[PDB]
Image: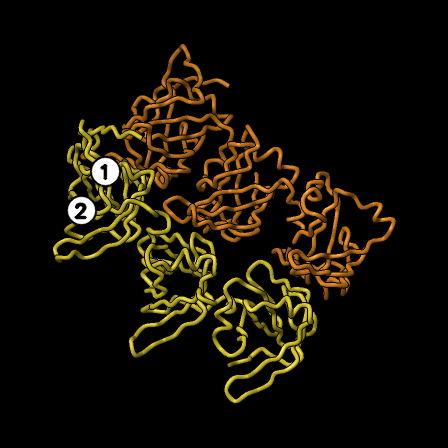
Chain colours: A orange, B yellow
Amino acid sequence: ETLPDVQAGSVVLYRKFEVGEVITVRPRANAFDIDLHIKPEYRNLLTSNSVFWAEGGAKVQLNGSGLTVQASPLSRALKGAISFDNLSGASASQRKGDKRILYASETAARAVGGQITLHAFDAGKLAVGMPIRYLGIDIGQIQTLDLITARNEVQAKAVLYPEYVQTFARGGTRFSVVTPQISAAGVEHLDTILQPYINVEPGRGNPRRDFELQEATITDSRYLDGLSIIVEAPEAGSLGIGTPVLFRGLEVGTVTGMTLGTLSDRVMIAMRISKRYQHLVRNNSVFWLASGYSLDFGLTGGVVKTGTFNQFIRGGIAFATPPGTPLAPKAQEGKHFLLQESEPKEWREWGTALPK
Amino acid sequence: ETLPDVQAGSVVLYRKFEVGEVITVRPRANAFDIDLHIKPEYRNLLTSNSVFWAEGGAKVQLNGSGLTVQASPLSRALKGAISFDNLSGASASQRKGDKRILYASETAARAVGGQITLHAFDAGKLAVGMPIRYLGIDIGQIQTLDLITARNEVQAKAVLYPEYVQTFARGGTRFSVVTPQISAAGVEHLDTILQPYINVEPGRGNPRRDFELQEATITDSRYLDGLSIIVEAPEAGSLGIGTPVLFRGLEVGTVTGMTLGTLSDRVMIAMRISKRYQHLVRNNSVFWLASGYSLDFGLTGGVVKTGTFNQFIRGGIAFATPPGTPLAPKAQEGKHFLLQESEPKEWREWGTALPK
């Protein structure tokens, strides 16, 4: 439909190596036609599962560290060239249209079946070419941004590479942007300042391939595949997303999210505890809010303490198990706990034996 | 009228592809004339709704990430070239003038009907080429800046792309710049430091196409299409634009603006509450000011708390609903509330059942 780069007389590439030749840009009223010459032995090597992608001009290929340019003839440097390669499931590209379609780049030539669609309310963080990462590994990329004013949202259509298209996009898949934060909570992300990406949690179910871009989550990356615990509290307090959960001062997990209840009388606080520390919680495991500095004034003599701990900056939930010679069973995947407003004196003196 | 780029002998482009040739720069005393050659089949393809835009020299096309240059002949690299394309409603460009007019760039060639005019008091943030964005999507651009000293203001004439010219500029459309902030309130905008833009709220009414650039608003972007609530207070206090409104500690909305009353005895504070949290407020929903740290000294023993919460930095309004077995109806689009100077003791013990 469009040929911005294509110039007549340019060279055909294969694995960034020259075999073949572009000869003709034959125009039509609705959709322009391009004609290519390749050798008779290699046209027998040509497959019906072949994709053609074009690139034009000279890219300096900056990319931070290395901006080298490859061994290039004057035929790319003067005229917009075309490369090609085979792949496994490219038969659908020949099912559609009358003839093969020339994709605008190598990324769009891999966009057969792996093309998904997101729905975001604010595209202020999104960008064209923004990579979708899983565990810091590039597994996808946004290629366009469509604004709709009929329903006031932005449809972001992205791609997934064909190795990960089956494992991901299975429904219940949470797409979340990462972003620089400057607030009451300290910043943990520095590469996102220069180059932001999208973290993703996989799911299980039906291949939906229609998604909603969720909010910026912090808990999910470091504390993953853990026991989900819901605790109901009268007040929010200094709690937030990223607030650590502490066991004898050791950070075992963090708060996933905060939501109003089904009845608006208690806020529910979702947390996850790590797998190695999952066994610590029991059905008798009382929570208490440990936020900020708590110190007791003294009349005869005044003892004061400034720990400069993390709970002052983000106010954490701390717990311990009361001693019982019959042990209560483990906490369920869904179970509600009652937070204690005061820190119980006894927890220093409990000494609860938790094996393994 | 002006031809800075045009050079005789240059090439005619179409979709960044060469067909045709510029032959003559024929001068006149008042307005210079340019003559173009195109092929006989393509001049039949030429339409009365065609726009011509010219670009000269070689642009490195830096643009942050990619600074590649396209496949270009020496005819652009030596001489200022001319491209063209059709569009739908370009008949007005041929109604004006004797012959077709050559626009200075591709953006000015799309500026037919979509050209609006702003009135700003200070053009210290504005710039030529500054994009007008809606939900982070580029939907417009400032192209010139005109200073008037008869009335001491700056007229900024901008463009809108023809897809969004009908949906936007409908009257009641609020144009507001975004800007880096370094003040008592924490900074949320980091891309604006490098590249500032203009956020816009659409409106409903008559196609005015004459606007006033409003002040830098913070509430509008994140908290949008919500229930507007006016609260009158004796004092301003630590309130400001961006100050959150809290329900049981959860941020449900923010303060839109602050204005003196019709009678200067009470300041009015405009806020919006989000759609999912809109049902929480009722006709009996008392406000109170929760700003800074409030702690009670103890004579026998002194309890102190430092939450390190957001309300210390920007002093928020918190509320809860008193319990009533007949429920009062929802808050109106315009209704005045009375802020309580002291936090009522009872709100912890209210336990008001708010469904859905």
Q: Is residue B116 visible?
A: yes
Amino acid, disc 1: Lys
Res A166 → quadrant: top right
The residue under label 2 is: B336
Proximity of marks 2 and 1: CB atoms separated by less than 8 Å: no
- At label 1, counting other C-alpha atoms closer than 10 Å, the crowd grade (few under 14, some 14-19, many 20 or more) is some
Amino acid, disc 2: His
Point 80% across, 58% down: residue: A21
Mark number displayed over residue B261? none
List x then y, in percent, for residue A347.
34, 23
List x then y, in percent, for residue A160.
61, 41
Q: Nearer the viewer, residue B192 or B8?
A: B8
Please count the marks in the image: 2
Q: Secondary structure at mark 1?
A: loop
Residue B302 vertical placement versus B88 (above, below) = above
List x then y, in percent, for residue A20.
81, 56
The residue under label 1 is: B330
| A204 relative position to B309: left or right | right
Q: Is residue A301 visible?
A: no
Q: Secondary structure at mark 2?
A: strand
- At label 2, counting other C-alpha atoms closer than 10 Å, the crowd grade (few under 14, some 14-19, many 20 or more) is some
Res A339 → quadrant: top left
Q: Looking at the picture, do discs 2 and 1 lie on one chain? A: yes
Point 51% across, 32% down: residue: A172
